[PDB]
Image (cartoon, rainbow, N blue to C red; front, side, top):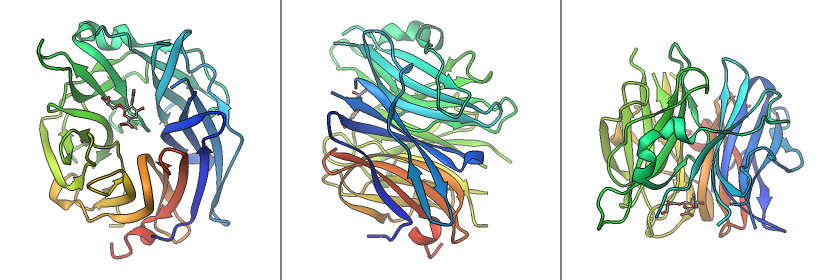
Length: 351
Ligand SMILES: CC(=O)N[C@H]1[C@H](OC[C@H](O)CO)OC(C(=O)O)=C[C@@H]1O
């Protein structure tokens, strides 16, 4: 497999089990925040990591529970972090469900002004963000994984998500991805329009001039579903299967996507299991002509063996001068969450 700068297990089964990773890079801090669900999802835990380039290593600090990220009598899950470059405020969106076909799922948000050391009490955004549609869903979720902040005038916040809709009384709820939008730095929220039928966990990234929001979602088909928004996430008109991006047997697996400075304005990177018959062999895919579906490359092998959920983060310029990437993924039959750090040069030397 591909040689990288670092490969370290940052979460592993012990008194508890860990799943559903989310990674967040803090530019001016040369630091990363690794989030995960702590299952008996009971709570959300976090680990802070400081990146030292000279040693090509991130040093991770002790694991700590995000105390405020919970609603009394509910389980917290799907950590979705975001760093506001405008205010220097950290956001952590998550889902809260009763300790135990009516919708009882809640959308929550906690914030930190000291880079994740301490958090505010949670804000239940459910009613104001979803409105009437709430009763038309069996449940919903955000992410999991890092969110997006657009470089539009308002520096809008974009939270990838999906909802199980009760479209027909005799049919089971059908999932459709969409984005929650805020144009006032998280004070108020709006529900964006749904992308095609049968789309689940997704992530968004912004490319390029025309501003385009690309959405990459998990589907129940043999390939990923990709959608494009030309109006900052409100509408995802274009939508199609991406045959080159395979989805494993059961009902696919969650994957991650980010944008990053092109060596030549931006390219896309995507990670997801590459075996067509199982969740194994984490692969990295490059799209040098985003968001063109046929431009997705062949996958490069990042990790052999059992691999599931993942999350990416652009970490700036790497030691070899090329784009540096951080990746957090579930491995070994969910026995752990591994942190992988590598550059574009290491993974796609021909590009
Ligand atoms: C909120 C929640 O339970 N998330 C689940 C997610 O659910 C997908 C879909 O909703 C199923 O119908 O899938 C998986 C999974 O390993 O496949 C792990 C997450 O923890």
